[PDB]
Length: 448
Ligand SMILES: [Ca+2]
Ligand SMILES: [Mg+2]
Ligand SMILES: [Mg+2]
Image (cartoon, rainbow, N blue to C red; front, side):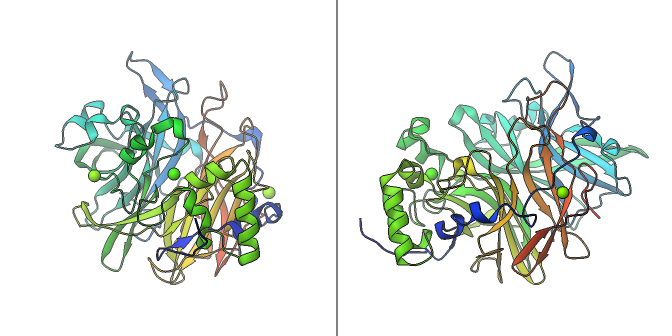
């Protein structure tokens, strides 16, 4: 193995940037705001029935608003809509997409109503599809309001029985209004798998199985599809991992200057450190990516594209892919936990949102705030005001985005269930971002 430099024509989250985060993160510029613990409520309408027909107060975690094509929050027949994962706090494998809704003008968490699950259990068996019949959980995605006024959902088909296989999936959700304050899910159609990896550009579950599966410490991902449009084309941007031809995992990746950045002396010392320490194996296996595919207008796969950015050597897990245009530029964001990173000074409690900017959709992504740090949340997982899945929601006017997240870990408290965190504001200006210090919003608030 010899030193080399191959970018594979894509951008990279680099070690030289990540190593600076520990000394940079303890600043009001990046810190997720301290939240008012005493006033946090559960989502009162987050109730579901189980197989025995008993009503349960649900945990409600990763959530996403129904968006216009440009990323702004849609208004659907006078409502804002939020899709969210939810289930029984007592069953960590009970995960379904629910549809919540609130009158556009209303603001309080109490004004969020629950239209119930998007899918019936029987729905997955209806279409002629190679994957849906194997689904065991419904994981996160995105939602777009089409120009024809249709509710178009993207989510992740997770299959515990197929070694944690994850498939980008879509459906149209048919809605009606039986009265003035109710939205009803009538059913779904055009329900189908879109993409489950190819092997060369993005890792497949089969690659995961063949290398030896869970015992290996590899973490296979293919999830959180986020819909965008760019000048007549439609895309999904999603969490994945590289395939064999765009810089795969492997001991050889540790010799690729592209993943280190900085200059030769840093690359030599950091490489040596990696090879001699207990991060070697995890760094080798680390090949996270924010992938992109183009879709046809019927939401089928049109083209598998090279990733926008990767985290080779740094982590296998860059989550909650998010991307939108602001000021003529494309901003790209991802959530990532320090516990899965291989960076000195980043620890078990550290959770981040990282951000990058490009002049074009597939162009070079450069880090925001020099290192790529946007948000830092380090509260212990037991903290009631622990937040996760931070998501930047672009706005119609101004330079602020709204950050949504879920609050309180799943199943951690008898009375305090995973719920909508109070939303907050981040300023975006060129390659700089800053948390807006003197404002907090309602729990689950999407727009200002
Ligand atoms: Ca990997
Ligand atoms: Mg504060
Ligand atoms: Mg396939």
